[PDB]
Image 1 (cartoon, rainbow, N blue to C red):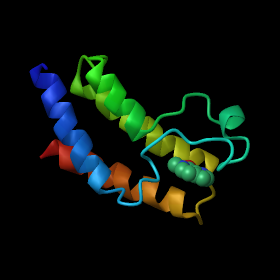
Image 2: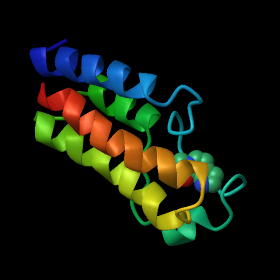
Image 3: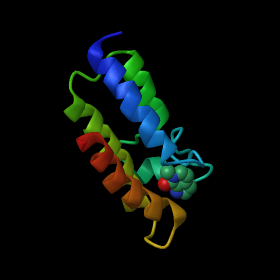
Length: 102
Ligand SMILES: Cn1ccc2cc[nH]c2c1=O
């Protein structure tokens, strides 16, 4: 694997530690989130991000960060603010960018 893949695998491991329940581990299904696919146009999750690293689809750290932000923004769009998912998305968006900045 390439230096970028190694760095992104490291960032991904550290980001997933901030989601110990694995709420962001796999794509959101409509079965657990009614109507999700009809509301969220560009779904994202950590498992898809892992597959993109392995496929070498991220050509910059910026692209990886954009998928992480997309994942969090989706949760803050579909869910109401008084939900576990909204609250965690907001928390990990900020904490995750901080972690990747230094
Ligand atoms: C990320 N995520 C995971 C599960 C779920 C159920 C309702 N909303 C959500 C959500 O946003």
